[PDB]
Amino acid sequence: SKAKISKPAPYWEGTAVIDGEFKELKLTDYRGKYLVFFFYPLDFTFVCPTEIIAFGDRLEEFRSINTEVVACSVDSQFTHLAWINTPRRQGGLGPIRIPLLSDLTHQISKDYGVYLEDSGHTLRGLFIIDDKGILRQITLNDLPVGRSVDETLRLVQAFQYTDKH
Amino acid sequence: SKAKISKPAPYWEGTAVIDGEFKELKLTDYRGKYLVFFFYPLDFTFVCPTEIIAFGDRLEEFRSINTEVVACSVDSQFTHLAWINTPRRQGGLGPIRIPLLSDLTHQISKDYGVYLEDSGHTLRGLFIIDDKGILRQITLNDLPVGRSVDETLRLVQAFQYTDKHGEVCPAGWKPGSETIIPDPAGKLKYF
Amino acid sequence: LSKAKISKPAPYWEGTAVIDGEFKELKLTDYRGKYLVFFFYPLDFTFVCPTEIIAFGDRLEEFRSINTEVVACSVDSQFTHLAWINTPRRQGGLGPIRIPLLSDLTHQISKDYGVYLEDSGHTLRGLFIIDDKGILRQITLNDLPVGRSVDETLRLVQAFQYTDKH
Amino acid sequence: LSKAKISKPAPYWEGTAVIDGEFKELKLTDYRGKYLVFFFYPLDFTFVCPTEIIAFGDRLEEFRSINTEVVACSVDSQFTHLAWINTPRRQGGLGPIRIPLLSDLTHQISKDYGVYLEDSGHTLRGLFIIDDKGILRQITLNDLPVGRSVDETLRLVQAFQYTDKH
Amino acid sequence: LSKAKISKPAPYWEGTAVIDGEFKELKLTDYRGKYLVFFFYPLDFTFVCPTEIIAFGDRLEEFRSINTEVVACSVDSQFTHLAWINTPRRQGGLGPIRIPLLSDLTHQISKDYGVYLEDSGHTLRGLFIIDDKGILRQITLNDLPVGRSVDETLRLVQAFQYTDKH
Amino acid sequence: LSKAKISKPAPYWEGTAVIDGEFKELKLTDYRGKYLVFFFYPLDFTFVCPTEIIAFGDRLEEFRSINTEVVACSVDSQFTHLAWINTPRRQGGLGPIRIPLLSDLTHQISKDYGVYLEDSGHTLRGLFIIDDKGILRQITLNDLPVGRSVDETLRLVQAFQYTDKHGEVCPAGWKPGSETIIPDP
Amino acid sequence: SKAKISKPAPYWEGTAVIDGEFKELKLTDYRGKYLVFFFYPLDFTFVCPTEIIAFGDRLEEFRSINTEVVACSVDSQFTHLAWINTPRRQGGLGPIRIPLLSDLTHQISKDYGVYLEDSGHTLRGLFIIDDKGILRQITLNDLPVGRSVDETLRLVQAFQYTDKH
Amino acid sequence: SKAKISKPAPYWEGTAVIDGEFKELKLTDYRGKYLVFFFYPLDFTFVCPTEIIAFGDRLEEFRSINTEVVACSVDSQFTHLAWINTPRRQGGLGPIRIPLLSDLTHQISKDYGVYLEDSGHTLRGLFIIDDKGILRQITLNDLPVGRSVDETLRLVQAFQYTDKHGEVCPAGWKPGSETIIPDPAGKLKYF
Amino acid sequence: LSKAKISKPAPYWEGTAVIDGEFKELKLTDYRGKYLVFFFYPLDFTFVCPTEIIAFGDRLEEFRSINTEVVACSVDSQFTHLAWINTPRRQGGLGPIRIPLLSDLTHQISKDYGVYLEDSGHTLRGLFIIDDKGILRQITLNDLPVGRSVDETLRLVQAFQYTDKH
Amino acid sequence: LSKAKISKPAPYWEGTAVIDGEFKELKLTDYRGKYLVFFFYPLDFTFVCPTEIIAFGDRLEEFRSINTEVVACSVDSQFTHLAWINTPRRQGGLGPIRIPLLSDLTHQISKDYGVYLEDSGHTLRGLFIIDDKGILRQITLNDLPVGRSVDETLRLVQAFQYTDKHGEVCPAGWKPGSETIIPDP
């Protein structure tokens, strides 16, 4: 893993589905803003949808504090798009306001230390990157357990508070 | 760093201050129970010990769910005891129910990947270890920002739940929330 | 590095496949005693219609009548495979299909067969004819834009079985 | 080790070929600007009739009409190649032939293309489709007993040229 | 390993020290032009350690009047050093002290002076006498149970200054 | 490297010493059961008076009365040691002496104790205190110009023996009869 | 090269054309007899035929002194057979009484130090192996120049003479 | 061993006895001419020096074709001179026209791959080197068996022929014999 | 490198020597129970070499009468040694001699005794005195232009036998 | 390894010697332009009389009359050398001596000349003859019990100087005036 707290967050780049289109997306696109960068195991599964939806549905609570959110898994951009176009009824994402980054090669997952060699996908990893691109926080969950939008919010606010004061 | 989620937590042992006394403490002493194992940077700094006290005050909430808590820093056991014997009034800890593990050699810190080579102490790292001694959760904070007892409680409850019923826990899940059946078909009963 | 060598035993593989809507464990050795056509395709859910997977599934009986099974594989998860199968052909989906779809999430199978694209994170179009003793007899590698011929695969299989016999 | 990788430049080769009864130097680069079907066969003067070399030579115009050349290669010397060509088809010879026969005496070409059999000292049946920019587009490797199809090679070439264009 | 060698420049150090109740950055080079008695002790809130530090502190003028300073050091943080100083001698604290207490939290300085105990995570009782030119002249290492002597130290400093001169 | 590490077994040595004017084989292990003050000095026969060897020799009974022996060592041969001892103190010689003079001709002992000066071919002034169990307790290294103190050496031996016996640790300057501390909070 | 005078001749084995048939042939098949073992560049060439024919046509002069002769090149056994079935008129060998060993893999040529890396075939190399399998003589010619049956005969006779006396 | 057919012959230099005198001799001294360079095992043995004498007696046959001859062994130049000064009657060489190169260091022998590590001298090795200093022919004999001047003459003539006319020489070829045109077509005019 | 070390067993040697006109195999161990003066000289048919060998040969009884033998050695073959012996002293030969002349054609012995000159292909003038127990006691190495002395050698042998005894 | 190789430059050395009772820095290069007899002996102050150092000292003028100097060396310190020289021959001492006694305290010189005995910490008896150009011409190594000969040393120096001058080589036993050989057939 290249991910070290208080060091620049490992650079990434790749294709994301953004508002239903394929776009190239870079970590550096987010300079000036805080970024919640998180990995989830696999599209068309179970815990991964709920926590992606929670974040998307509450996106304004981040954007209103100069914070953006990006989600990532090892699935392809085509699978991401198919998942978005799958209605929440059938366990899809439905439309989403958060970019879904594809880590097909696994390079990004490995740089961030969240790749599972034995499974071929990531664990539940979340990274808080500040506006200068420095990594400030790392949350790694074993697969069965989702993350909390409220705890994330609290942490972003705390770093912004201690940044200032 | 030997700490890997879903592998056995890196073994450790050392001197801890427990109820005012020096006691030898081992990771294996906690087999059978969940363990919240966390590091904080330094004794005796100018910031009020809000997090260690918060875990100390709410310790019964963890014990009611088969969970113990252990705190650790690179300070000596002697410094730990001195800090405890210092009134909260003056930045001390005052009495405390949670053992304070000493990591003078830095070995434990390095094994958990929380040691800061440039500073000579740890960042704020917390680890949730299950009753079979498997590591389930890693939270690493930059120095300025403290940890939440509630969030820690939520995570411990969620792991114990999914241990038991297998069903997986959605984002935000607290006790009493809807869970998911980990099946492409069974998942519909939730979505 | 690639372990696939003609007239040597085909590189062993195992993983999760989707067979008739369900997740099943599948191994190379499950096909001992039969010829196996083992082929890789890049990705589920792309905008190019699944002509070849369907062509094979539609003509599967021409294979089973000559003691030959067919298996398809990509780097997609078994969950994606299922979702694709459960998407109507109308919308680029696969629809029901009679061929197992094997998941190579870890990329280990793709690497062993030398079909993995390090730069792209999926495979090219590789097809392998494995005999009933588990020996690799044929290797066909296509650059992405160009599909494979069921008729050619049939001809090759029949040919190998003929020269096996006479 | 093999240097042949799809969507990379085909491994460079050079040597002596027999072209229309004569010895000529020949290089991969001589075919820049054209598609090239480059194929290996085991050995001259064996007791199995030269069905495939002849099939290609007989249908060579179907290739030249789509900007495609054909080259055949084995580990035999150019002298053996010539002697084979100068042997009547009646007696297993090749007879006159319109395809260059390239000699790979040093085995270096066979190794670079990953078709050499260390144990046997000749190659298997390998065929390679190289595009007009010298990029490798297709790899077909057959175990010895089974030949190649001119129709399939045509279909593949046309297909690559189509997707090049559209 | 230890960089501390008699008759060679003393291993450079720098770090945070508590000086008259405040955190100051302190370097070995701040002592050029003066003799320096630089000594390590194990841990704050321990037993011999206070008594040795108190003795050197209380008799500091006997050093300063021969152009000699004194610095003490342990692996304790500067926050622990300051808390110890603000502990009344009654309760085993240092009480106010005139000698800087250097912090070696990273262990780098202890290791450079060869006094660190890998097994225990703190130093033994090492004392070093460094001349005004920055040259190490004397090394004294005691096992933990036994304290050093101000009188012996004074005698040594005087002996060196005398032989320097005559 | 130097093998001398405090609270580890002192590096084994053996060699020929001059003892009461005779050549004797001497081993570090010969001193088990007693404390040993083992010290190096540079060279026999220089133009600086042998103040420190004589001082230890003259006061040997204070060491012996506390179960403690003394051995001196330099890189000189045993023949040079003997010649020096047979030279009258009047003429810089040692005169008779009660302390063994161990010869370290091969330089191995000096190297093992990390007192050897590679550029000079002799040792600096090093003194080592070894307990009854063969464990190194104390290392004193002096640059060449400055000698050692019998009183300080006596105090250290007494202190280590006191702490061996009572555990209680010895404060700065502690001498026999002074206040000690129970290593307990 | 493994070929050293007064050491056992490097072991070889391979397929030869013997009286128009393919046979497996081993160096050890010749124990009890002297062996003239020689390499020539390529079938369907120029100097190689004449010196093979000279040896074959004078084979009795070797067999009458307990000596056998084997020829070798990198050509395949199929090319050897085609060459034999090519009439001397057209530069073939015509029928031949000497085995033609195939060194398709080049292992034999390399063991004997006669392989030409740059050309893919051997130079003109001749080895005299005694009846105990010890190498006694080595003759290496650059490609333009044939060997002499008379000189070979003289050498075999000399070794047999000095063996005895 | 650095001797490879169709590569430049391994360079050498040393002291040779030439017409009773000690002379420094170099391989490069023979550029422009063919060189027959041969090794024999030892001076002064109980076997009559039939081969060195045979080359000495027939030396004019080589010089008439732009070819020199040099013999070499591991013996010193002093032993070489002594051997020459010994009457053929008594196993000596008696006077001789061919230089005798000394290889005391064994370097030259090792470079030509003729040195016998177990014996400390060479086997019987002969080397034919052309006028451009390229090695054309290597003949290695076990100790018991001598070399033929006629065969050496034949080989030198054949190389000079094929150098000149390119046409290749068939087995047994002596001057005046049929040669072959090195072409799949031109070869018929011979066969 | 040289294995010859004073007070250690002399490096074992063996080889062919000319002894009274005949070739005999000779080993260092053939001399156990006696002192051995073992010396090297450069080359047969040279200059100082004969004179030194002649002197030791002519005065051999002075060695044998103190239970000491003498062996000489050069890199010359045994055939050269014998031819040299059969050369009249007039013509610079040795003439008949009573000392074995060991041959070191392979250079192995010279190298073991550290007397070989890589540059020249022969030895310098090295002399070794070996006791009756096979222990090397003395080494004398001279540059080529200067010969050894029988008297000095005798004196040394006598000195060693005397100190051995008393 | 030993760096002493015949017909190669003698291994450079420098150090402190006692010369006419004074400490002087001495370098091998100080002897360029003259032959040098450089020899090692084991130890100062033993119970075997200094026969060979005295013999060389007593006969020094025979060396000096042929452009040849002599230096003796042991691993002893220069202070020990001085004490030994100041000890009367009566008492095993050296008494005054005309030959420099070079000190090899660090053992480097002894090691460079391959005369050092690792197990003993001193040298065997080695003698080296170095010409005016710094080239080593002769090596004589004796086991400890047996001393060296001034006459033999004189003969070797004379021989090397003769051959230097006339080329003609010197036969066995050659002394000044004896028959020599023109190195020509």
Image: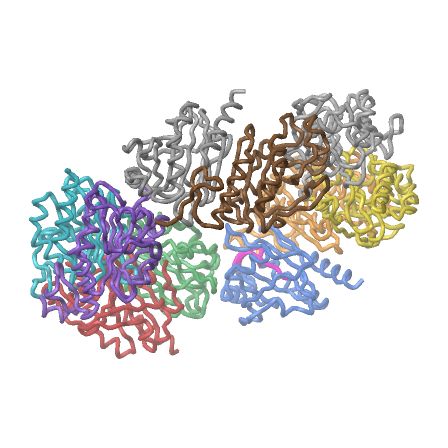
Chain colours: A cyan, B purple, C red, D green, F brown, G blue, H orange, I yellow
Q: Residue at x 27, y 45 (%)?
A: B43
* Residue B154 covered by magenta stretch: no
Q: Nearer the viewer, residue H139 or I123?
A: I123
The image position of residue B115, as x and y in percent, is 31, 47
Q: Nearer the viewer, residue H158 or C11?
A: C11
Q: Residue at x 74, y 44 (%)?
A: I6
In the picture as drawn, the residue positioned furthest to the front comes out as: F177
Q: Is residue A106 visible?
A: no
Compared with A2, C50 (above or below) is below
Compared with H127, G29 (above or below) is below
Q: Nearer the viewer, residue A126 or B132?
A: B132
Image quarter (top left, top right, bottom left or bottom right) of the N terminus of chain I: top right
Q: Is residue G114 visible?
A: yes
User: Picture quarter containing residue F80?
Assistant: top right
Residues drawn in magenta: G37-48
Position of residue H167 in the picture relative to residue C128 (left or right)? right
Q: How many marks?
A: 0
Position of residue F145 in the picture relative to residue B108 (left or right)? right
User: Picture quarter containing residue G51?
Assistant: bottom right
Position of residue G110 in the picture relative to residue I101 (left or right)? left
User: Picture quarter containing residue G133?
Assistant: bottom right
Image quarter (top left, top right, bottom left or bottom right) of the C terminus of chain I: top right
The image position of residue D155, as x and y in percent, is 25, 61
The image position of residue G56, as x and y in percent, is 63, 64
The image position of residue H113, as x and y in percent, is 65, 49
Q: Nearer the viewer, residue F177 or B176?
A: F177
